[PDB]
Amino acid sequence: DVSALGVRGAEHPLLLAAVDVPGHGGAVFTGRLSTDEQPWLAEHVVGGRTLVPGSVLVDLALAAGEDVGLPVLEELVLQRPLVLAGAGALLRMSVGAPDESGRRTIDVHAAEDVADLADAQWSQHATGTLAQGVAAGPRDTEQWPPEDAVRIPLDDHYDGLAEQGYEYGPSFQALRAAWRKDDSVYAEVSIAADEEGYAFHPVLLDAVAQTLSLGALGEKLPFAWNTVTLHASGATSVRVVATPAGADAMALRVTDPAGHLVATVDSLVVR
Amino acid sequence: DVSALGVRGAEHPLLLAAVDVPGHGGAVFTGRLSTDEQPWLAEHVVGGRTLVPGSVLVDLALAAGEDVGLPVLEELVLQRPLVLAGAGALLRMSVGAPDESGRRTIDVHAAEDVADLADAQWSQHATGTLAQGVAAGPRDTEQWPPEDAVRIPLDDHYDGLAEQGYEYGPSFQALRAAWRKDDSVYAEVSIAADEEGYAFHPVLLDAVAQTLSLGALGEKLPFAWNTVTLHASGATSVRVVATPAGADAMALRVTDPAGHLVATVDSLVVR
Ligand SMILES: [Cl-]
Ligand SMILES: [Cl-]
Image 1 (cartoon, protein in one colour):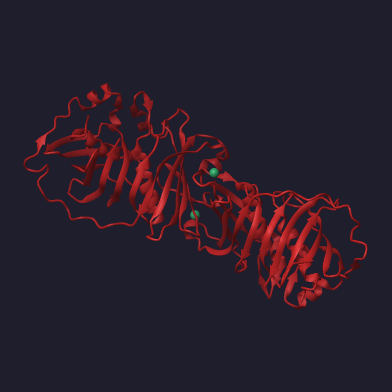
Image 2: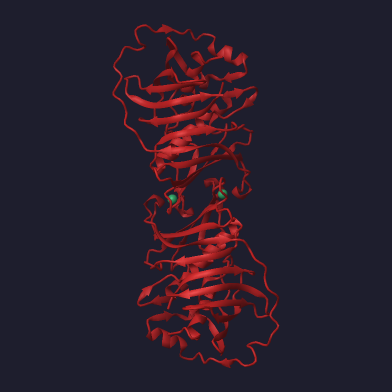
């Protein structure tokens, strides 16, 4: 039925079809987001607007990279957040030709949902670069959290944020425990398993980025993700170490509860 | 159902879906050819092989240009003819980003038919450039054929060609009358109406190119089409004036029987 239209079907929960560009090895991906299909979308509200979390675009870009064979998100810069309008949103990712180094540009567009794709009013929401896979470090066997780390009490964490206009519903309240040492933050982050097929579940990935609120940073929204590497897919329960990385940024190291490396982010920048 | 997969449906008889690349204004088109659906494919046999006529790729490229908004085929260079293998063939056309002049590259690939598009063994069959539309000349009101033109008898034209290994079945025997003056050739060319939705019906367009066999050229296969402009779609009956255009090439001017301009080709080159 997908082959009947001459496209490939996409396994990612948010994607519908993929089409290769045979001459340059790129590809175009189409998908659709809506609160009906992904009710957790309704639980990320910022200043009164239902905003799609940037982590949705990061996970989709990782899925695109894995499909095209360039699985590292060397950079993704988020423009305007997607504002979810009851009607849902169409998504379109384009991966272009390789540069001399073998890297490719990826662009991400969205539009208000329409019946006929010719009518889609695309706007650009992100752009970045896909690159080659890198090896995983060794399993972490050190005490968790580290010896001198002290508990960060989380009791009114989400209440506090809500006051400030950042309203995370239970689906996004995924910081389960946290500790601090110097300006490093250690956290256990987990969601309930649901859809398979994400590269890194975007609710889980947003909650990984939430660790930045617990450090010297916490008093914006992430806007640039730099060197995102994925070593395991399908995680719903991870440990995160967030370390300072220059102004308005932290590096992230994400493992499973057994210490195996799951993902790294050289710097996540807020603005 | 097409919108369900996030693509646009294609009106061209050989195409299945189209997908825009919103960032650069290009697009990717997929389709499929087979003798079951287009029985005339079986009637173009060259040296014993069932070869898809180059005019199929030219018509598809014009359809792509019209869709993207660049309706002139500034050039199309045909590589290896597509050899039709009982299983049919998949087709894929990619239109890229505009150059500074606003022109775009178009690539055409084909593969043996497969159930899963991920398995498609694409090979490149043509590449060219799409450009901006140009105005039509005035209606031709001159005597047809011109006053001093003499009949070219056509009686064993197709028999002769068949001897030489070029076997055109009745569907392609579309040269209905021809005349010559100097090295110019005038011809009436027509097929029976069938599928709508072609930019220039590829059987009709191959028979337009057949006029090159009637002139000082006629004793190969066209391999480069230079500046193909379309002023009318849906023609099944045309008049053709073919004029010498340098070595191994002729220019073509194609009108309806009322003299209105339908198409021009600055040079069609054989090799
Ligand atoms: Cl494909
Ligand atoms: Cl589209």
